[PDB]
Length: 60
Image (cartoon, rainbow, N blue to C red; front, top):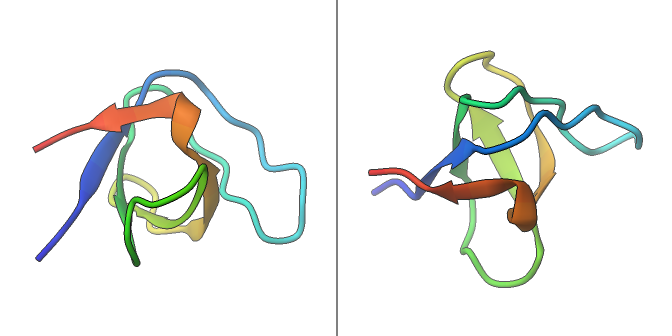
């Protein structure tokens, strides 16, 4: 059970709860893919936080 995505663009953390990531990073969500902001964990960096769905695309 995973739901994974790859980053299309860099995203710099700007809030207390979001997650910085670089283009090409692999990210997994910790709940469902509903909505526009998802709690994620980066397989690349090990960090976690909310990410914007419009910066990523599904990755098997």
